[PDB]
Length: 206
Image (tube, rainbow, N blue to C red; front, side, top):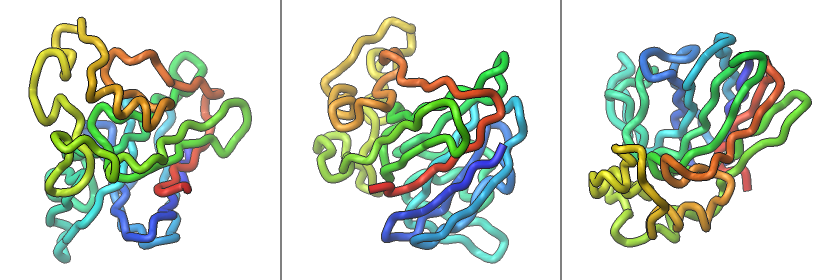
């Protein structure tokens, strides 16, 4: 499957793509404002994610740091990124269908649209100004809007037991972005697409 990753933000981002235990394609790349990077993701990939990273520095060997979404200091991510990270999430070719969503469970850094480029389903978007409107207690001094699990490490925010409800913090993310997951047990906003669809992830779509 192809994923065209497009940076419509006015600032550079470093895109990242991983399934947690391995890179997808090269795993990451710099995207200046307006640049597009097309990756290939193996069919059957389960639990893949794409995200933006901001305010990064890398040496010539591809080692460094980002202020949001850093994946072990690598340009080419092999693992998931450090919150806050708006997440484009997907599982491909799962019994004949693909499944896509956007999640704010690991916080929010950059607005994104995640849409098919092929027929048969709709896209999802979280493009509101979550960082600007972020509750004081969730603001990440490094940049972005943290989720409450990250900040407070409770059973209720992290849904550790599997019994949790919505919270005043999850409801903030849900208000700003109804079509993204706001906590682990949120009413799903997953879209079913045809198996082997292709996609575009756009940072700062609006």
